[PDB]
Amino acid sequence: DRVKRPMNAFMVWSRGQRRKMAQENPKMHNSEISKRLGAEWKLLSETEKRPFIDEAKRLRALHMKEHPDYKYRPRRK
Amino acid sequence: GAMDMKALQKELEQFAKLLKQKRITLGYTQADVGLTLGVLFGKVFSQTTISRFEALQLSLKNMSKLRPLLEKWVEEADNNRVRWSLETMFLKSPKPSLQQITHIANQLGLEKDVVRVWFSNRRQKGK
DNA sequence: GTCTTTGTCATGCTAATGATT
DNA sequence: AATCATTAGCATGACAAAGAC
Image 1: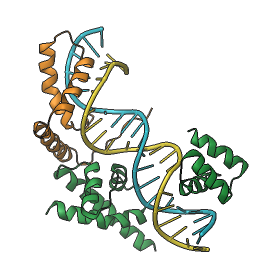
Image 2: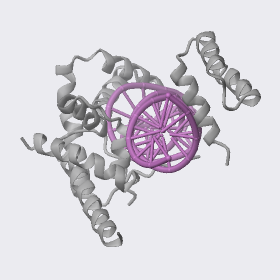
Image 3: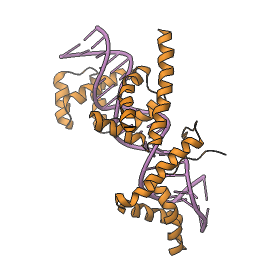
């Protein structure tokens, strides 16, 4: 029921890559997958990132259509 | 007056909502908008002031000043330690001598301007 | 609920600038 | 050329995925 934030480029990409890295290394903690995905994403070229950048753009636009009155309201400590 | 106020307020609540919808359907971050104002007028704005414009948390005077630049954006898109030292001088001399100011600037590797401004900001902090 | 990452947006504090002297 | 109010950004932190713990 609560509206989540839309998924930025890295996080879109990181979904499919997380699944493959879990398959390749089935003991690896999600914490460690994350460090490795960070390192891999920093290395990707601008051309390699573009499909993921456009998917995040597309999901932000849809987020607005789905949730016209949405405001990001983070909880302060 | 009050009539000019209500009208200007409704105008901006309305433009800010257009600005947000347009930057989203065009795939721009707040950051991108600030940076791209910089490219098209040579005048960068930070992600922060774009967050505050869209949430109506800037002053109505501030919104009015920035709204033209942003309307042009919409158009084109469619086609410590140093502080410690300064505190201790403030305590001894709240309004400092011009000579004292220069001394502490070269002493801490700052220019005068920063130093004199620091003291003014600190004076205003008494409430 | 916590490890973990990048990117995006929100906010608290204060440096910097504008307005008016 | 010098105060006081106001504008503005830097640093920071939340939160989106995943699921083992």
